[PDB]
Length: 298
Ligand SMILES: NCC[C@H](O)C(=O)N[C@@H]1C[C@H](N)[C@@H](O[C@H]2O[C@H](CN)[C@@H](O)[C@H](O)[C@H]2O)[C@H](O)[C@H]1O[C@H]1O[C@H](CO)[C@@H](O)[C@H](N)[C@H]1O
Ligand SMILES: Nc1nc2c(ncn2[C@@H]2O[C@H](COP(=O)(O)OP(=O)(O)NP(=O)(O)O)[C@@H](O)[C@H]2O)c(=O)[nH]1
Ligand SMILES: [Cl-]
Ligand SMILES: [Mg+2]
Ligand SMILES: [Mg+2]
Image (cartoon, rainbow, N blue to C red; front, side, top):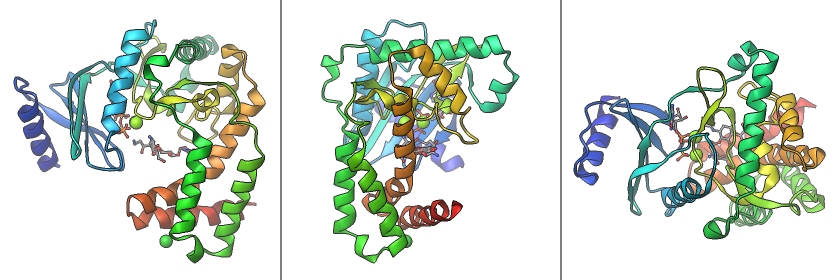
């Protein structure tokens, strides 16, 4: 563990001239990134060359747009340090203090505390979804079209070596993709990874901050409800997302659920595709196995 930290301490001090690292520890990690807490005060998100090429660039542009344009008491990252190159990206900002929302914590809250948190969330999403996004119009994401392109990449690579059961799962998804209407609604700026491990609470169990707008863009309004609607051990549950949808208002709940259900069905294929693009066999295997788990669950 000691070695990662030394290397990143060196890089931080090297690229940010007057910055002195008195302490540094690993605070989280993704498949291709590592985040560090520095001087018990700064978060530094870091990445070495992936399929970002412009990964931390977009994320930084989104923080800069949001810090200019949001009116909210909810805190988000405000970038003070950035280094962006092809081979290395680093973003630093002051750590937002608080406690991440979990299902356990939620279950200890009174009904009223739960209501007020749901309202805070609905309010934040209403404010962000309502922004005029002209000044960030580069950050458009078309999920349907992305899936089509990923399907083509599958066809060009490993599709012919998949099993019949795997192929059928994929084709059955594509048929559903082609029949759905859930990509034809309102587009807006969405966080696009809006799960409870990105939501911070203050000492009264109210929403105090939101992190990791790394996947944000102009996309279907339904996107920001995918995790709030998810029924799993990591998320609070379907009722939570429904109530939030009612508070948010002017949105078709049944289509939001259809959108989540389609995204969930896509997951094993998304996983396979990630493995192909990043040359990681392990993801290809995991996604294929998951197709069997889902096929046999009923
Ligand atoms: N950054 C590390 C965060 C941690 O690894 C994590 O929570 N990682 C995430 C764990 C989730 N169980 C995965 O699945 C999530 O999304 C699926 C659809 N996208 C849902 O059907 C699923 O029900 C949900 O659970 C999710 O895809 C993982 O997301 C991570 O990988 C995605 C690529 O697939 C990226 O796009 C995300 N930015 C990143 O958070
Ligand atoms: N308390 C607190 N924790 C934070 C803050 N920013 C980051 N973290 C912590 O660091 C972890 C990683 O941050 P995050 O932005 O989600 O990055 P990532 O998802 O691992 N990487 P990427 O977004 O490049 O794929 C978070 O899960 C959380 O543990 C912050 O402002 N406050
Ligand atoms: Cl495999
Ligand atoms: Mg994250
Ligand atoms: Mg992220």
